Structures are given as structure tokens and as C-alpha cells.
Length: 124
Ligand SMILES: [Cu+2]
Image (cartoon, rainbow, N blue to C red; front, top):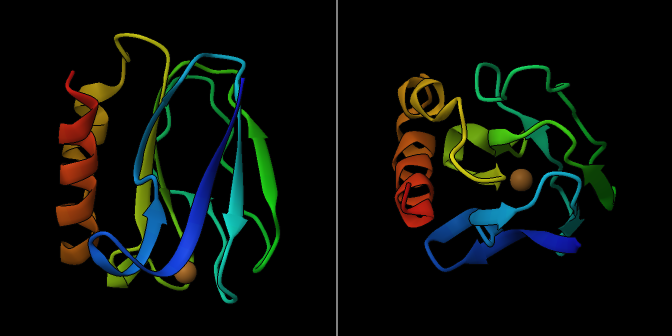
């Protein structure tokens, strides 16, 4: 199954957001990260990927398709806007094994508040 996540100058929770900020997909599904507005990318947050996952970083303005082969929860950021809160989480599969590591990982305040709301929305 194929999903999209958008990089936006403005959205639900204010400036510099991914939408949806919280998504559940199955292992093997794809997410295309679509910069609706100019100036965004996607990159995994160091410490917020599961066992055997590869880190990734797209170029600015790239429509970037990821096939999520390793199950678990992923924290993602936009590289320039991370510190302004531009984050998302992708849960790949059921009962993610790294849920504690992701809840506990250290992030700038604005990113942590948005990560916590995205994690809460997953309802683990
Ligand atoms: Cu951005």
C-alpha cells in the first residue's frame, strides 16, 4: 500500500509541519514525502529508527519515496526546520519493538512536543 506525507509551511498545529504527522502503515508499504511548499525535506531522526533500519535523508524539494521494510516506529524530521518543530512519526506494523526508545529519544522542545502528540495519536 502506498501513502503520502506532506511537508508544509503551515498546517493543523501551526508552522513547519508534516501532515499527517502520525501515520500507520504495514511493513513493506511505501510513503512518499511530498514537499507541497518549497524548502523542505525528510530525514530520519538519529536514535528514532528500529532494529536493522537504514537511516535516510532526501534533498530539499524532492518527492521522496521510502519503502518501509524494517518494522517499528520511525521519527522523521525536516532537516532545516527540525528545531522549529517539523517532525513526524511513521509506525510500521503492529506492536513496534522500539516504542520505548522512540518515546525516550532526545529532541528540541518544539519537536518533542509534536513528536509526543504524534506518538499519542498512534494509541499504542
Ligand atoms: Cu521544512
